[PDB]
Length: 226
Length: 32
Image 1 (tube, chains in turn green, yellow):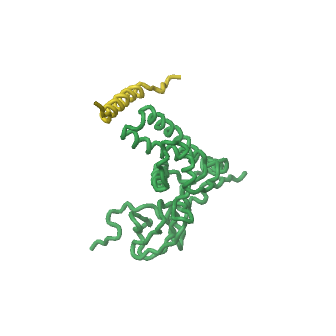
Image 2 (tube, helix red, strand yellow; image 1 turned 180 degrees about the vertical axis):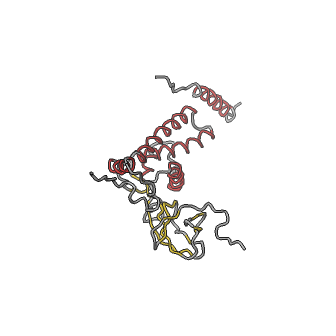
Image 3 (spheres, helix red, strand yellow; image 1 turned 120 degrees about the horizontal axis):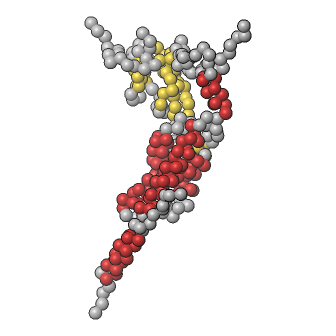
């Protein structure tokens, strides 16, 4: 992402929607739900807050933080060696290796019995209220506004209170801005294309960046003169 | 005599269906 994510409260999206006199029955409560549907459906990893927590595994199980949304990596605390993924069907089960993890709910399922693990994860940024906080990006803000205008107009079109030409314009305009908003958040900055440059140009290919926290991923590869 | 609450709602509904036909001919065209 080229621009920085400056945070603003959710009611800044309601100044923009209630400029439209057909969207004047909108609420904070409706703006809360349609934001989280929009934040999810875009899947932009720049909208989330990166956190790291150390949890302790009791017997192939550990309790996961409350704010966790997606795990970046799980690693061991004493080694720093990262855990990949549990493909075993019979993991902590005895009959009569490379460590792994698996997460379903608020429980993580590891391959190690009694160990502390660091979990680097993503959460949602909150307010003084326990409410979501959105980027002030006028591309993000415009297409979140067009998201809610397209969900409200879809209800109104089912009711028969909106022209099919009106909904077709809103469905088209949200469809353009959703790609512009995707490209706004995905396309790297100059400082991220340098780390992409160093990963791409490697005379001796570095193929074990998952073992670290992808720390040396964008590091530059140097060759001695001889 | 006179009472016009069913003459009104039938005339208001005929102008609604005539308006509904007019907004169904609207096209935002998509050639250059």
